[PDB]
Image (tube, coloured by chain):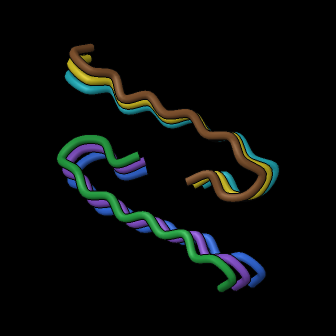
Chain colours: A cyan, B yellow, C brown, D blue, E purple, F green
């Protein structure tokens, strides 16, 4: 779209 | 898009 | 895009 | 605890 | 605790 | 604690 917002997370514990 | 915001996080404890 | 705001983090504790 | 991790966010769009 | 990690973010678009 | 880590951010676009 006009702006694209992407977040990716990896964790052993507590990826929120 | 016109702006792209990208965040990648790796963690053992806590990826917020 | 016109501007890309890319961030990467690696940590044992507390990626924010 | 031994370490306290705290995150607070305010947004109009796209708070993650 | 022994260490405190505190983050506050204000945004219109995107708070990661 | 023994050490305190604090970060405050204000933005229109993209608080990371």
Q: Position of residue D10 (x, y in %)?
A: 30, 62
**The N terminus of chain E: image quadrant:** bottom right
| Above or below: residue D8 compared with residue A9 | below
Say which residue appears at 42% left-offset and 68% top-offset.
D8
Q: Is residue F5 visible?
A: yes
Q: Is residue A1 visible?
A: no
Q: Is residue F4 left or right of residue E10?
A: right
Say which residue appears at 37% left-offset and 30% top-offset.
B5
Seen as rendered, the residue at the extreme top is C1
Say which residue appears at 55% left-offset and 69% top-offset.
F5
State which quadrant residue F7 falls in: bottom left
Q: Is residue C6 left or right of residue C12?
A: left
Camera-side residue of A1 and F12:
F12
Camera-side residue of B15 and F5:
F5
| Above or below: residue E4 compared with residue B3 | below
Q: Position of residue B2 (x, y in %)?
A: 21, 18
Q: Is residue C10 left or right of residue F5?
A: right
Say which residue appears at 36% left-offset and 50% top-offset.
E15
Camera-side residue of F5 and C9:
F5
User: How many numbered marks, from 0 up?
Assistant: 0
Q: Position of residue D7 (x, y in %)?
A: 49, 66
State which quadrant residue E14 falls in: top left
Camera-side residue of B13 and D12:
B13
State which quadrant residue C9 falls in: top right
Seen as rendered, the residue at the extreme front is F2
């Amino acid at each position: 779209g006009l702006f694209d917002i992407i977040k990716k997370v990896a964790s052993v514990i507590g990826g929120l």
